[PDB]
Image (tube, rainbow over all chains, first blue to last red; front, side):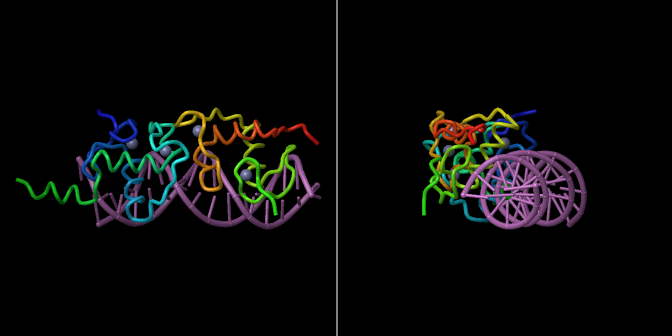
Length: 81
Length: 74
DNA sequence: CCAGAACACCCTGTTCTG
DNA sequence: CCAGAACAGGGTGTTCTG
Ligand SMILES: [Zn+2]
Ligand SMILES: [Zn+2]
Ligand SMILES: [Zn+2]
Ligand SMILES: [Zn+2]
């Protein structure tokens, strides 16, 4: 019953190594598999929350990285301990 | 040959009273009618240019109004 | 030439499947 | 539980129509 660490929406589980909602889970996967040459229109600190997370993919992706999301998370936990 | 005064894309003609591109023309009309209440994720001063105009409809719509865009101007 | 409508795509987020 | 795929919708921008 926790909150997505990236956007504070209703979290759905531990995804790519972090507590997140589903939207952030698929957003991160899409961002890492393509290019993430996104551009912030503000000052690289946009507020990423449930209604505003769509505004700035640049800052959203940055928060994903900063919370520790990574593709090999599940496979890394499966080497422990 | 010219420049949209809202997003700086190549403008297409005078729309709603102002030199704008086509995307800004239709954005503005949708903003006034659909009257969604948009919310900035920054500080209400986002850069509105070709690639970023889509990031912040609140600020884009503000820049539209500030450039003089107006529905009943014809 | 411009307003408005239609179309066509992208991005997103929910649901399905392995 | 959680990854990845599929599917459904909203916003955006170009083209079409009045
Ligand atoms: Zn989230
Ligand atoms: Zn940002
Ligand atoms: Zn424009
Ligand atoms: Zn803004």
